Length: 46
Image 1 (cartoon, helix red, strand yellow):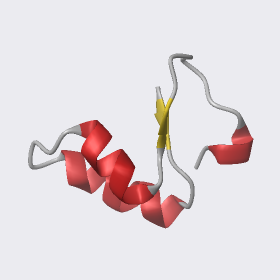
Image 2 (spheres, rainbow, N blue to C red):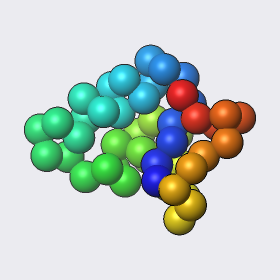
Image 3 (tube, rainbow, N blue to C red):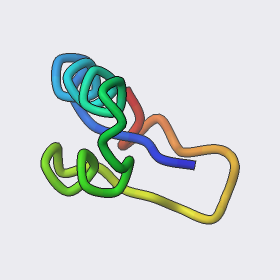
Image 4 (cartoon, rainbow, N blue to C red):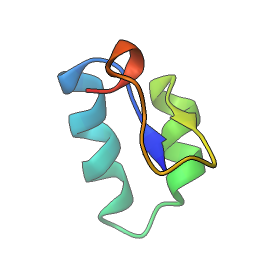
């Protein structure tokens, strides 16, 4: 599960994966984290 900070940052993160851009790439661009768990803490999830 991938969870990003800032609702704005995660917004473009989602839009990033729309054209077929790899999730991890967009995550690296947003300062986003990809954890093995299926639920992220609210500390770093927007």
